[PDB]
Length: 279
Length: 278
Ligand SMILES: *[C@@H]1O[C@H](CO)[C@@H](O[C@@H]2O[C@H](CO)[C@@H](O)[C@H](O)[C@H]2NC(C)=O)[C@H](O)[C@H]1NC(C)=O
Ligand SMILES: NS(=O)(=O)c1ccc(CCNC(=S)Nc2ccc(I)cc2)cc1
Ligand SMILES: NS(=O)(=O)c1ccc(CCNC(=S)Nc2ccc(I)cc2)cc1
Ligand SMILES: *[C@@H]1O[C@H](CO)[C@@H](O)[C@H](O)[C@H]1NC(C)=O
Ligand SMILES: *[C@@H]1O[C@H](CO)[C@@H](O)[C@H](O)[C@H]1NC(C)=O
Ligand SMILES: *[C@@H]1O[C@H](CO)[C@@H](O)[C@H](O)[C@H]1NC(C)=O
Ligand SMILES: *[C@@H]1O[C@H](CO)[C@@H](O)[C@H](O)[C@H]1NC(C)=O
Ligand SMILES: [Zn+2]
Ligand SMILES: [Zn+2]
Image (cartoon, rainbow over all chains, first blue to last red; front, side):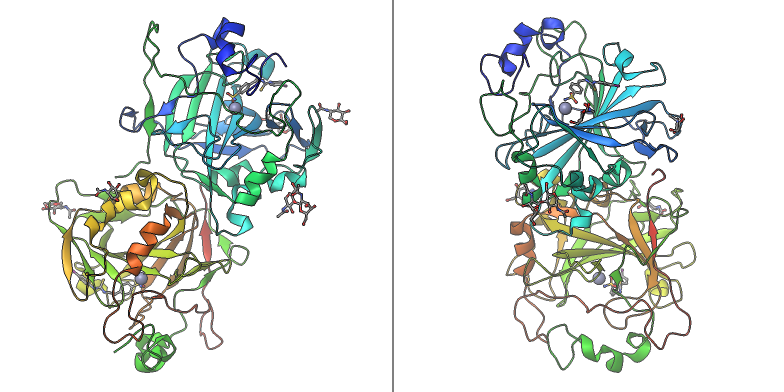
């Protein structure tokens, strides 16, 4: 509402001035994920996403004016980074970033390459913090998974990411206006993760990619994309932007690339990478 | 003599010309049916791993029916149980593709054909001392099926051809049968990391070319690795062998077989694996 992607008064170039804590920082996201300048760390294990089977509550999705954001009910979806299914990270939401055109859209790049859509699965560190509102603002409170998606011409519906999303229960269209929300069938996040290799990813400490760009995010970005069709990406593009945006249709809702180590950093960060127990 | 495209020697005739075992009831490929398969949680992630002290060369041949990578002995292995103790040793990798982008794979998944199916062939070194003893004996072989799908937008480094090191450029019109060329080693571990190695169909079946021996433990990964139209067209530049009717190599896949033909004496089951978590 005080920031946008496309209105030059409030757009990404202004965030460092409008939200200095912390959009002016030097641990910002997204970054270029560079295979050659990253350190392989064999101790980083396969990611698991898993559901509390006795959870009953509804999932919703909202056009928040900046993105399409799925809101998961509490105590329902989890991430494990350590092989133990003990509720260390609890998923809160998933939102999406895409392009006006198929050659751009993602926040992260991989060796300079932009994907048409990047999904962000946002969790809080339940191991330490009892609620999301406690975690969102505090050191080390968040972990986000970045899921790239690529467009293919030939695929069965059932093998695309939209199958895991249950097609968003058909809710995406021009009438889905900010700030409306709608109930949807649940997203099968375990199926989504099975559509890529969950051992192969970049890992680094960074930030939220929208203001206030808090530097409290443990980032994991999977290298292999899940697959969607051109028709599916088009469903996002019919969403309208909020009125504080210049462009009418929602698209190009991604932040410009940040450096891993701007010149003013007082302690450099390292980009790590993981791969499966093999090779 | 056999072929894919000559109606006189082609797949419809294999059951008669090679009755052992192309007339059997445990033949491959099959349609891999998600709904009519049994999830078996005990089936673990597949690992491919290299003996880092091997230095022997890899080669590729146009054998007249496919392009076949031949790996040196004692070099590349598969583990299905998480232990790296050389139970399965990889022998070769070959490929099946179509004249057009909408067919080419031997297996289907829920009826869908992919443009290119790779077959990583290994022998059960746990029981048999050499590829030549395992290839015609019970339980001798295990093959991995790798589906590939065409994308328009991708960097070369993220395509399967990075793992293949472009086959050192040997895929071209002048690569005539039965020439063989030395190639850079194929990074099969990287290839496997391009898909989810816990998510696969598993069943007992057969070689997909004569003599169709019924001694193959099949593993077919569900998620495809990615290639470009340019890359698929390289395979289509290869010439077929002189006993094919078609000139350029393509449609070198066997028709779909049933999991359980009517005459079967003991039905087989299609299994499915997925990663721990859900
Ligand atoms: C997935 O969701 C979309 C809606 O977001 C469905 O698209 C609709 O298709 C029918 C016409 O056959 C009409 O209701 C509308 O023209 C479409 N909506 C828009 C905006 O395109 C689509 O059918 C769904 N797909 C599946 C497989 O369920
Ligand atoms: N693009 S990104 O992935 O880097 C990113 C992620 C998240 C944010 C905003 C945080 N707000 C949340 S999750 N609110 C919230 C959380 C719990 C509850 I109960 C109510 C509200 C910004 C950017
Ligand atoms: N399409 S398929 O994947 O079902 C399939 C069909 C046919 C074969 C049999 C080929 N025999 C081999 S591997 N001879 C061989 C033995 C030792 C050596 I050194 C080199 C080669 C294998 C796989
Ligand atoms: C699982 O769901 C039940 C009922 O909603 C809930 O009371 C329980 O706490 C949940 N378990 C978690 C969050 O680990
Ligand atoms: C979502 O929509 C309804 C109906 O318009 C509204 O009353 C409700 O408070 C909204 N809830 C959320 C999740 O913001
Ligand atoms: C690995 O290769 C070395 C040297 O090439 C060889 O002597 C050794 O047997 C191999 N290890 C195996 C096959 O397990
Ligand atoms: C493989 O193919 C393309 C050539 O057009 C290229 O960009 C890539 O560098 C080649 N790599 C090797 C190892 O030859
Ligand atoms: Zn985001
Ligand atoms: Zn084969």
